[PDB]
Length: 234
Length: 234
Ligand SMILES: Nc1ncnc2c1ncn2[C@@H]1O[C@H](CSCC[C@H](N)C(=O)O)[C@@H](O)[C@H]1O
Ligand SMILES: Nc1ncnc2c1ncn2[C@@H]1O[C@H](CSCC[C@H](N)C(=O)O)[C@@H](O)[C@H]1O
Ligand SMILES: Oc1ccc(CCNCc2ccc(O)c(O)c2)cc1
Ligand SMILES: [Mg+2]
Ligand SMILES: [Mg+2]
Image 1 (spheres, each protein chain N blue to C red):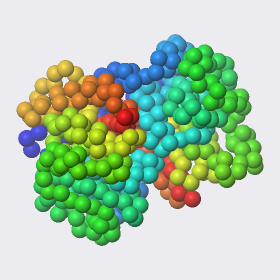
Image 2 (tube, rainbow over the protein chains, first blue to last red):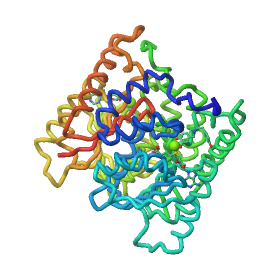
Image 3 (cartoon, rainbow over the protein chains, first blue to last red):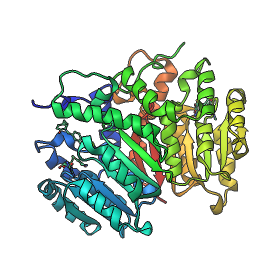
Image 4 (cartoon, rainbow over the protein chains, first blue to last red):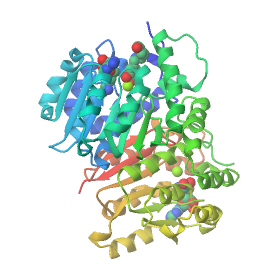
């Protein structure tokens, strides 16, 4: 009623997305992930929730690459965070960052019931100052295997400049929402809320930049709202 | 053309697909992959060609899991095979299986000029006999890291029972076309060629079976025509 893109999906039909969720995603969704999702769906910002089919995709990536130490930028109620914590080994460690811990406390009971809260170091701050402080203290043997970026959309390019130094060589950086409900496909797009237009132009610039960035290999994956996987080359 | 689905997209517009390919895939596509794709686009069976954005996704998965030995079932002109060979290290090895070597001869010059043909063992045969002989010969030290299944659609479930024993624990099995142009989303779908309808039902059964299969964790990804990633648990 205030933002324009919230009822749009990138697949050709709602029926196909429902088929995917019902056939493949929900039967593989942890019970605490199911709980966190269903309370979040009643929250006013439920449009920002990472969907269940994308969540299982993040879980698969974490396990295939044997991730141990991860960083999560943009937590909200914690669906992707809890997804990550359940995918990591028992000794896995996550640095979670979000300006608003009130959202996080919506999901924390489910994280606790899942028995994975011990893996999480939550920092209530803006992401950039923490990443900049991490650049001064980071030791080469302390680099992250994996980074999920899902915070302020207009700041992804700034996040990238830090994360290509905070993630190990061969580690992964994942940028959520890089297709922005399909609106990135046109130079001009009508009738968006000013912040949705800022994010749209930001993603158009980020997609072009990442495609030309020699520090990484990339794969833009038309899952959820678009996820761009980056792999650090040096 | 006899098939009915060949031109249907699973994204909501051609413009979105073309944005992804033009922005994120084509600029990252190896020169020999581009040449192979262009020749194949002129072939009568170009519909079955793995698309460029999915190719980068397959390549990203291989590198993040540091795959070294792979199997490829369903080669055609070799786009995904070349993709796999370019991702592997210099001493990587691939077993490629297809019933029609003449398709493979179309892309072979591009594979050779990429300098990666030495990694490929091409077997001109039906996949099931080869897979069965592989299970009779395979030692635990020889198990594959990664398997890409993209051959006779109605036989995926049969391939699956062999491949869950031929990929290592923690190894990945990927099935192509698991969304089948979106037509899997409904119990019935009018206007299909008979063997288009057989594949559709075979994928509907396959997707339900894979979601319940305790031997693997899965992730169905709405990229290309749908890719289902399986990871062997035991
Ligand atoms: N500058 C900033 N630094 C850190 N977090 C920020 C931020 N600006 C916005 N955010 C947070 O980023 C989140 C985006 S919604 C994130 C969704 C979440 N990944 C999921 O799994 O569902 C919001 O919770 C918002 O509070
Ligand atoms: N029983 C069988 N065993 C092995 N290959 C088969 C087969 N039946 C069909 N095929 C082959 O499977 C291929 C499917 S098209 C595969 C496309 C390819 N993966 C790409 O990257 O473009 C065809 O080449 C067909 O010849
Ligand atoms: O300042 C904004 C930016 C965008 C909107 C519209 C969509 N709401 C944000 C959103 C949507 C999906 C996500 O995945 C995500 O992280 C966030 C509203 C206010
Ligand atoms: Mg998001
Ligand atoms: Mg295919």
